[PDB]
Image (spheres, coloured by chain):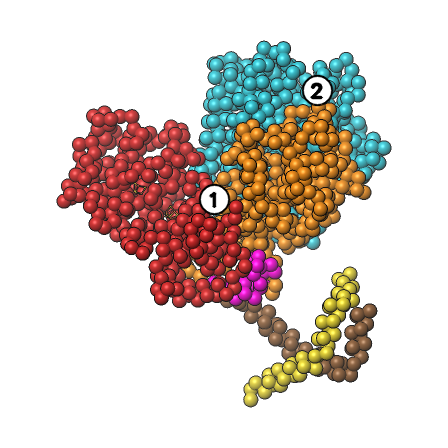
Chain colours: A yellow, B brown, C cyan, D orange, E red
Amino acid sequence: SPVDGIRRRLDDPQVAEALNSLLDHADLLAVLVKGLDGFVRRGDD
Amino acid sequence: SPVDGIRRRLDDPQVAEALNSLLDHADLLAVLVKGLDGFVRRGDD
Amino acid sequence: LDLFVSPLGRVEGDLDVRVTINDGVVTSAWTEAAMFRGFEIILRGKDPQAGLIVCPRICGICGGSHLYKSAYALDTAWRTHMPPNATLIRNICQACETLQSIPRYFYALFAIDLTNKNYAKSKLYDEAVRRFAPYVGTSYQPGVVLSAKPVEVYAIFGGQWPXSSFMVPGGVMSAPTLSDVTRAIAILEHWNDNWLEKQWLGCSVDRWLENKTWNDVLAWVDENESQYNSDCGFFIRYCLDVGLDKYGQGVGNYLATGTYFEPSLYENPTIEGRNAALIGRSGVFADGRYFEFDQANVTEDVTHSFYEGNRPLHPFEGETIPVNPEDGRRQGKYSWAKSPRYAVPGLGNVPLETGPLARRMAASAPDAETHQDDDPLFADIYNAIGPSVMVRQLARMHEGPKYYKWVRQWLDDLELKESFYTKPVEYAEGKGFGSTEAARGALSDWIVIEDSKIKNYQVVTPTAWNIGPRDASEVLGPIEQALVGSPIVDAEDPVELGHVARSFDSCLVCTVH
Amino acid sequence: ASVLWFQGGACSGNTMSFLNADEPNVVDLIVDFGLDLLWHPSLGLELGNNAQKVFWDCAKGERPLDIFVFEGTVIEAPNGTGQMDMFAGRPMKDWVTDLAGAAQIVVAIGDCACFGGIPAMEPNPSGSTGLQFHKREKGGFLGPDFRSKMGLPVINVPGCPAHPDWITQILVALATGRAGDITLDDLHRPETFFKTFTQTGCTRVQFFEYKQSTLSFGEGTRTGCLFYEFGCRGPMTHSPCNRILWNRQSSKTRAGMPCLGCTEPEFPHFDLAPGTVFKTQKVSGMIPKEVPEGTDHLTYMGLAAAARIAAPQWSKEDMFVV
Amino acid sequence: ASVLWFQGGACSGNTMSFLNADEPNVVDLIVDFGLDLLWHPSLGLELGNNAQKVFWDCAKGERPLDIFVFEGTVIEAPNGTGQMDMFAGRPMKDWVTDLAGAAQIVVAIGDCACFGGIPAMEPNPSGSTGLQFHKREKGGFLGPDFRSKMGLPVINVPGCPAHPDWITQILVALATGRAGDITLDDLHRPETFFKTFTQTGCTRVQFFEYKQSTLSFGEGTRTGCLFYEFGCRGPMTHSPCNRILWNRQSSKTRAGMPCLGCTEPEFPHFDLAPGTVFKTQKVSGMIPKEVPEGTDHLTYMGLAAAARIAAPQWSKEDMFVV
Ligand code: FCO
Ligand code: F3S
Ligand code: F3S
Ligand code: F3S
Ligand code: F3S
Ligand code: F3S
Ligand code: F3S
Ligand SMILES: [Mg+2]
Ligand code: 3NI
């Protein structure tokens, strides 16, 4: 199954480490996308 | 299991909050990637 | 005496021949194709055009033929349009590959056996050795060396030979330039002058093609010293002296699927319109009678082949499911060759010999259209002396002048400003039949495209026709019956088995694919 | 220098290509360069027991074996028995074992022998593998650590088939005392032929430089490079196909056929899966999935846009005109 | 088809190149393609009055003259008398007048005949000119409006010398009924050979694309393109030198020699003035004075900078390795 192969990659130490580090800074990603959303909804202004 | 390592990281209030805010603006992410896809398929033009 | 000859080389692949010998004569024969690659298995599920890449790799010497028929299989499956130039280029390249095969096979694969010690008593033996000894023969070296020229023409149009895939549904990939055509003409004329006419014939191609009867051929041999001492004249005299005209008769029934479409008649390839469009006519010659070739009559039997199966299968429903040769031999199977049979009315599913002789017999059929090969020579030879190693070889060699003339004319026919390719619709579904006459005979692809993938891909090669084992009725394949009756002077070097198998120009990589 | 040329899961295309040799031609190579061709299934005179006598003498060391050329795959099916390739009374793989162990030099000619090639395409019914490679993975049938008696690994002359010069010039080099001039790349290919790319000398590189695509076959190939629409692997394929022309005439790419990357161990690439034959797989319809060797998608695409902007008019017109 | 091949201010290089013809070779062209070579100074049997009889019969129309090939320049010095080229009792230019007026087709082979070539280099002591061109300027000796009896202008097969195929394939085309397939460019060169550039098929175009320069001759030419440091005119020169290889082997550029643009009417370019031989003239030491055909210095240089920055590693290493 392809989906099961992505779950297999998610069981790889290095992939897991990177995904964990992404989740650690997910707040920064969230804030940058929120900032972009804000900038977009104020693009007329 | 590293996939359950990140399932437990998905039980983190702050990580959950950021992931929820990302899913709130997923439409903007989708549209920017669609815009990039469009720009790429019109890159010859 | 049960004699197992392994390997019987110079058959482009892995062949073993088992023979029962009684009183110095083969009384029964088994041809054992010993090497399996399973390209039909590999092609399943691949891109619909994967055949254009894979099928040439069935065989080095006749891959261009594979390409030709695979391309036409796609053309029919996809109902493509073939611009006349594309048809011409395909014809030219198919014929050029055959023109390469003719001397390359004759000198490198066949004629060196003419130096066998069994012929040491022949008055022509010293000359045979001088001419045809491997690598040093005075006919061997120029024949083999010049055999590369026609495939230089092939490479001009296809990029390379072997292993181009430039024949695609809708035409050819290439766009010949003026210098391409002029160089192809120059190469062909040089090869014709230097090997075909100077060495093989000792006369012009036109003079050879004037031979309409066996008596014409004998008169041609005796006509002058040039023809007498030509490789062709010497070969005929050697065959008559050493008895190559006396065995290797075979089935006496022939299959030609034909090839070389008249460009105006096959612009929209279909299975049904194929026969009428052929220049090198199709035709089945069975029980002394001419029949129209119909691919629907083609079955493949695996009773004595190393494949699972219980009934002959038309290749559109063909299957290639190998069985382990140990188990298969326990079941009486002895060859990786399938047993192609042809349903001839009043005869059932019979073996048919394929090859140049089959083509010449087909060319002797009545009611040839203007574009079609109409040649009574081998009807006359068949009626006069019948098939044999010599007659089979002479058919092969006779194609040299004929195909050279056709290629020269096709090169003249190229309209360089016109299209070489009509972009086809790559239909997700389709059933294609592509056939050609490779150097060794009827080569055919039955392809079934489903869901934009190869659903089925069945190749039936000429040597599979010739060398394929006994069918369910235990009827020997053409090469097996040709081996039967062959004298065996020396069981330690049973060169006559080689003469018979190689007179078919057997290609075992093609046989099995 | 004795040469024993065996064919396993071969189509004999390497032999036929080899027979197209010029300078030297095959006869002059066999006779006049001191290369004693002991046997070749397509050319050897001996059959049956005489041929087997030659083979057994080579295998057991009764007579020297300087060069063992192997063409075709090492067929191991069924079940590792190799009986889908029975030759001269043995599975061909057993002959390969013995003769590769006996030879001074082992040359795998053609992808089948080098890497497994087309027969090794899935599902690989014949259990085919190369002599020292299975596709890119080193080891093949003989193992990664196999060395011939001259210390060399299997010399991989890839291609499907190999060009005659790729083998004949190596044989001449061996015969003329220039074996030491032969350097092999990481795939054991002669670097004298395989440092260049197929693209090297391609008549369409100027179109490539300016990102002008051939759009269609036939007359459409009077212009353009085949990389963008026909999956040309020229820039990702090491070969001298456009340096040393095929049949002394042409090359696939010159003729308008995309290079299928046949000198590369992955050939046939993508196993000819649907949509990969004579097509360039693209991301978002415009970025090729595979960019030329040594480039990255970012730089390659930036330079491609710049080149498209800078492209001169002639690069947009037919050039291989009648 | 009768052919009369005359040499004016020639070095016979076009004849020698022609004699290198393969497919067809020269003998097969002369014999087997129905081209009756009436005379050739390097090959004709007749001498003296017998040769002059042949020439006069061609000039006066006593016998048909289908193709008049002229090699070498039309020498007009001294003082327009042409006596620096006396042939068979006349100034060669007078023979040219008569025979060009008599021929069905006139073919100038080699730059000398096409455009004046090397002898027309200043100070042009021989008063050399081409048949229908003096360098790029149309008209040469015969005038811009000269047409042979088949209506064609002088067919210019340039080069110094012309490659044998450039003439032999034209002769084959004429002999095989494909004269109508022959299209001529603005310099009357066969477009089947002169739509491509020398660069077309050059083994160094990838280096050109990535602006990787050959830095030195000899082993330095194992890498790089010769355009930047050696004045390669490949990208400004129409020729099939890298498509149809010289001597079926190579080309200047492949071998490491810059294309001197010899198929171009200005050859030798810059009249070999000091500093222009095997050197790229540059502005401010970085910008080539001449950019490839159809390009502009600003887009070329911009693309060149982009290509340099995105250059792969292999483009910066030897590729034509031993
Ligand atoms: N010729 C040939 Fe090969 C065989 N048999 C095919 O088709
Ligand atoms: S030419 Fe044939 S032997 Fe293998 S390398 Fe290609 S399938
Ligand atoms: S330059 Fe040539 S090698 Fe292929 S990628 Fe373009 S056709
Ligand atoms: S497919 Fe192979 S023969 Fe050359 S042109 Fe490509 S490396
Ligand atoms: S080769 Fe000689 S004849 Fe003139 S064109 Fe060059 S100097
Ligand atoms: S690509 Fe070749 S033609 Fe000259 S400009 Fe460079 S060496
Ligand atoms: S100097 Fe002339 S011969 Fe060709 S490589 Fe340049 S156009
Ligand atoms: Mg089959
Ligand atoms: Ni074959």
Q: Answer left or right for E55 relative to D157.
A: left
C318 or E110, which lies in front?
E110
Number of marks present in the image shown? 2
Amino acid type of the residue that numbered disc 2 sits on in the rendered structure: Asp
Q: Alpha-carbon neighbours of circle 2 within 10 Å: few (<14), some, or many (≥20)?
A: some
Label of residue C176 in the image = 1
Q: Which residue is mark 2?
A: C493
Vertical position of residue D238 compared to residue C472: above or below: below
Outermost residue, bottom side: A45
Q: Answer left or right for E84 relative to C482.
A: left
Residue bounds of the magenta highlight: D285-308
Let me know if residue D293 is in the magenta part: yes
- Give the x, y percent position of residue C201: 51, 21
- Give the x, y percent position of residue D65: 66, 32
- Quarter of the rendering containing residue C468: top right
C138 or E142, which lies in front?
C138
Position of the N terminus of chain D, as image quadrant, is top right
What chain does mark 2 sit on? C
Vertical position of residue C56 compared to residue C506: above or below: below
